[PDB]
Image (cartoon, rainbow over all chains, first blue to last red; front, side, top):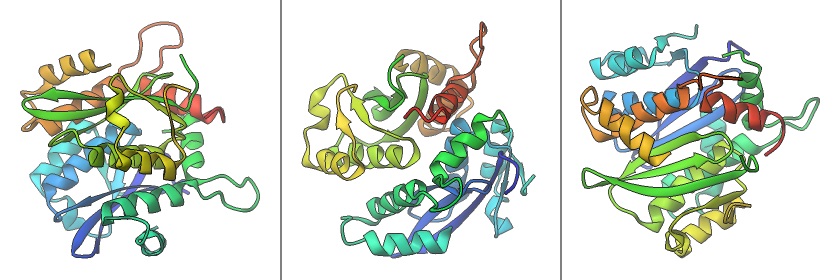
Length: 142
Length: 142
């Protein structure tokens, strides 16, 4: 969809807890983490992990206040990430479906991420989001 | 070095805390997490996240007792991971170097992972571990 270095990052709420969700816009690849509460500290930490794993250039969110803390700005500065774009409902569904097999929300979320990233799109060039991100980035794009 | 689906997973100790470290044997790519204590619960959770991100087939460790819990076995079973192979000192050094700039061990570890995964090997085909893993997997190997 967009440039290989573009990511979307938002927080979802479930069972009182908060689920931090990062989506690689161009591939549909998801990466998530369950955290106690929405704090700049947690967002900054998550951004750093994402940055050391993929070539993160820009991150966009649907709630700008999410990135106003000095903690976040500090993480972005160090990692060389700039703001604004330069599967939450589905994921929530899969979590709901798998929540029985999982003994905790954390597990259910990671089971849902696994499922989502592995599901091959039945069609032309039927790849999975997990495969797509690797390919997209492999082509020295990001 | 080895097959694209092979990973090494061990726990390191620093400042009282435990650092879970996963290394993609064939690329040198590292992925880490700082945790309170070495428990099967934490190892199982980490394995699940790694599995939904990369095509993890086999995981090896230097301490077999690390994978004897039913919790771990349960994670491996669900994710389809089998045992035994089918940069900790360097990382520890980088952490030591960056620990000043980082306000917490967690941050220093993620800064060290970023640094390690991004450092291009000055030589023939000078790629970074981060680039190597993507390429290795991109070639539909794993």
